[PDB]
Amino acid sequence: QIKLQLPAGKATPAPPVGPALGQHGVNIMEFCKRFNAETADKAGMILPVVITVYEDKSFTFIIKTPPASFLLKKAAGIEKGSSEPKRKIVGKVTRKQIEEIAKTKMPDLNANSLEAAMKIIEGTAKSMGIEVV
Amino acid sequence: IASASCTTXICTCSCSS
RNA sequence: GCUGGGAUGUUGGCUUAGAAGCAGCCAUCAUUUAAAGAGUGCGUAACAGCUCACCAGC
Image (cartoon, rainbow over all chains, first blue to last red; front, side, top):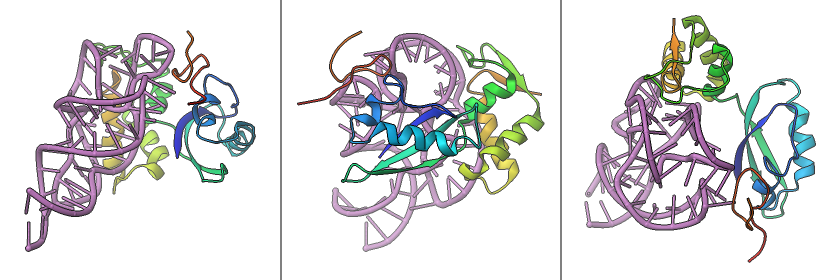
């Protein structure tokens, strides 16, 4: 069982994909087209998928919501997180934005309340030099 | 920049043993 | 002491070919918890895997 974060509508490259699971038994081509199939509904974003390979080299994979750090980057309109979180703020997002992301990632979050969800997201923002306003 | 089995971003990795 | 658990965002941000708790720098929050560090050491190319913290039962 392998896991990785592949961009929406794109796959097959050797450096990014290939070698990775391609060395566990997986047949790249089938995944590239397959992944890029459903990753059509949500394109442009980087989404993490969990590939599972059965003894017979066959496989399946679940597509999850994009990473918090990623959504956060997007929200703050930045490209990278601070090189020194807290010491240097490189961006910021509104409390409502935290709410949006928390809502977006909810299926993958284990919070029992939207409040707890936002607290989770804020923890990530605090780790990448992104402030909340 | 080269090897067999051993990196994440250029292209080698592994492949026997 | 023994057994079982040791979870979720998440491979935290940066860096890097990679850097996924564990080269290095910064941060070290939040969730679900009975409990579980943005992780004690081993380990991998990076993962994996083993181990410790912590909790539970005996």
